[PDB]
Image (tube, grey):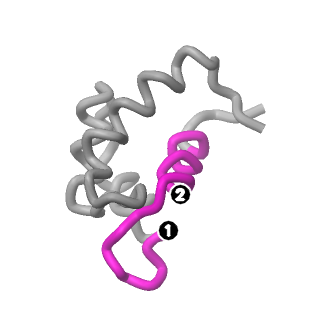
Amino acid sequence: ADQLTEEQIAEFKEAFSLFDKDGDGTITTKELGTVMRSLGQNPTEAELQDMINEVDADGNGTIDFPEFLTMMARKMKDT
């Protein structure tokens, strides 16, 4: 299940909404670094490339909404 407070989801929606202007909820991997920067997050370039190559398995250059959300959960020290 989600491990994010419901109020945080409102902000997360507005950040993704400004970039998923493609119309069905997809963002490009070239702007992938930009959405996280708008949210105030700057991870290592090594992590940036790795989180992209795990989900962009078909190399289509697009990332769907739940994939990006999974990666944002996966980078923490879980319990």
Q: Amino acid at mark 1?
A: Val
**Residue displayed at 41% across by 63% down:** 63
Position of 58 compared to 21: left or right?
A: right
Q: Would you name the residue on which mark 2 appears?
A: 67
73 inside magenta stretch: yes
Q: Which mark is residue 46?
A: none
Q: Identify which residue is drawn at 58% across, 49% down.
A: 70
Q: What quarter of the picture does the N terminus occupy?
A: top right
Residue drawn at point x = 35 percent, y = 69 percent:
62
Pinpoint residue 4: horizontal percent, then vertical percent. 63, 25
Where residue 12 sits in the image (x, y, percent)? Answer: 44, 30
Residue 26, given in percent of the width and then of the height, sits at 38, 60
- In which quarter of the view is residue 2 placed? top right
Q: Is residue 62 above or below residue 11?
A: below
Q: Amino acid at mark 2?
A: Glu
Contact, mark 1 vs mark 2 (Cβ under 8 Å): yes
Q: Position of residue 77 (x, y in %)?
A: 64, 34
Region in magenta? 54-74
Q: Residue furthest top?
A: 7
Image quarter in which the C terminus is found? top right
Q: Quadrant of residue 51?
A: bottom left
The disc, 1 or 2, on the residue closer to the chain's N-terminal end is 1
Looking at the rendered structure, the secondary structure element under dot 2 is helix
Q: CA distance from mark 1 to mark 2?
A: 7 Å
| Front-most of residues 19 and 44 | 19
Location of mark 1 (residue): 55
Q: Nearer the viewer, mark 1 or mark 2?
A: 2
Element carrying mark 1? helix
Classify 75 as above or below 64: above
